Structure formats: C-alpha cells, structure tokens
Image (cartoon, rainbow, N blue to C red):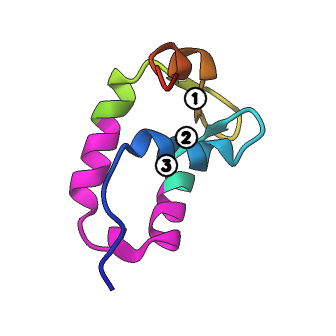
Amino acid sequence: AEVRPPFTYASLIRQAILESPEKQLTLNEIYNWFTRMFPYFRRNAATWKNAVRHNLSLHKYFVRVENVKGAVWTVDEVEFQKRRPQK
C-alpha cells in the first residue's frame, strides 16, 4: 500500500486551483482537498506547507486576487506557460 510518489506539485496546485472558474483558489481550500483526497498529508504538514509557501512567493504565475470572500490563489497560463517548455 505504498503512497503515491512525490513530483512537481505545480501540477497538483494548479489542479485544485483549476477547480475554480477563473482558476483562483485559497490555500485553505487546497489544503482540505490535499488531506481529504490524500491521507498522506495528515502527518507531515510542516514540510509541504513550507515548500508551497516558498514556491508560491517565488512562483510568479501564482497571483492572489483579493476578494470579498478572501484573496484566492490563481495560476495564469501565460506565466505558467511562460516557463513550461513541454513542446
């Protein structure tokens, strides 16, 4: 019953965010999904939350649109694709 292997979270973070229409979502909503979908986050949450925070500020494709319901994290295919030479 090994757990899924670690990889580029940029694909998992954009996914939870992609769950929205404008591709914008808060971290709290992504965290619930992280543990809710994968129980492998119900223990070491001090290391992943630390990398996401650092990668978030350094990631320019991650923008926080301040909203009345709280700012949300959104990814722009322009910035994200600006550094995604997948072809």
Reading the chain from its start, which is encountered first: label 3 or label 1?
3
In the rendered image, residue 66, in percent from the top left (x then y), is placed at 62, 26
> Is residue 84 placed above or below 55 in the rendered structure?
above
Please report the residue visible at 57 percent of the width from the left and 54 percent of the height from the top.
29
The circle on residue 75 is: 1
Assign the N terminus to one quadrant of the image. bottom left
Magenta residues, as a range?
Answer: 31-53
What secondary structure is found at the residue carrying circle 1? Answer: strand
Reading the image, the residue beneath label 2 is 14
Check if mark 2's residue and mark 3's residue have beta carbons within 8 Å.
Answer: yes
What secondary structure is found at the residue carrying circle 3? Answer: helix
Looking at the rendered structure, the kind of residue marked 2 is: Arg
In the rendered image, residue 5, in percent from the top left (x then y), is placed at 31, 62
Looking at the rendered structure, the kind of residue marked 3 is: Leu
> Is residue 24 placed above or below 37 in the rendered structure?
above
Reading the image, the residue beneath label 3 is 12
What secondary structure is found at the residue carrying circle 2? Answer: helix
